[PDB]
Length: 337
Image 1: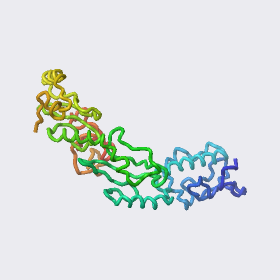
Image 2: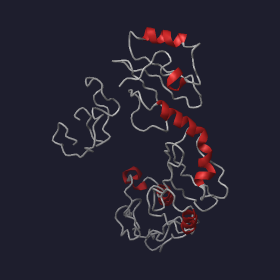
Image 3: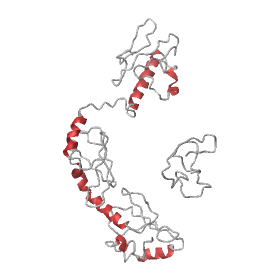
Image 4: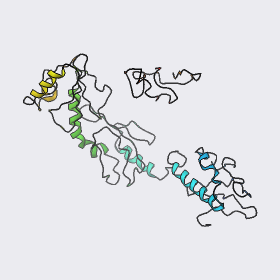
């Protein structure tokens, strides 16, 4: 009962419902609370106390608790402790307790300067944007962690790579030589990346146009009015790939016949534009203004290539019209942009 309350048990003259200087080692809040002399919920401090210790910053769902008036004298303290423990976990989201003065940031600068700052992008202790180092088209990423400079391996392993392109087994948090320690061994995936880049050098199709080095999508669409969905998502395969190139409706017969007969003339080692692309005679071709009075809302005016809807784009505006509202997030679809 009384135990576990490092700051509680006020003057018993009028209940002593203060409990000043009570916290779970994170923040010793104030005692700006009243002692209700009634049956229950006489004079609380939820949004009514001084709040000198940042108590008023509690903008959570206060109505959900309802002041915990259903409980008893002990139930009130139980609910208060539960709310405090719940708010202690939420602190990880905000930045009201990230001290960082653990001496690791200072020691991290030594390892950071040891590399000579070859290619750095991020700063402010967030992460290092070091990538692109390779004998071909380089596209990588970096980040920072919490236990940097200590035995805690850095968890900010954000970088373009396959489903297994991620290093582990941090030998005492080896910060320096990160590109050579684990980035040099990435040649296995770099070879496939360069092969895909060389295969996608020409023959513009309806496949992913934006940079998708982390993934793979085969969209030839050489046939007029159709799109050959010959995906190349398979990274581990050397050559001899095949996708569902269902571009032309009637052309499915000749393409299907060429794919069936292509079994003998597969040309796996020459499938890079020879046995796969041109194997079966395949040539590469060449402001949130709604309707109601609430018409005030901003939106990114950079590009609206898919402003018709969030999920649907370039489809019939009759059924699939209101895709989503990611630019405003209000009660309105994308049928007006």
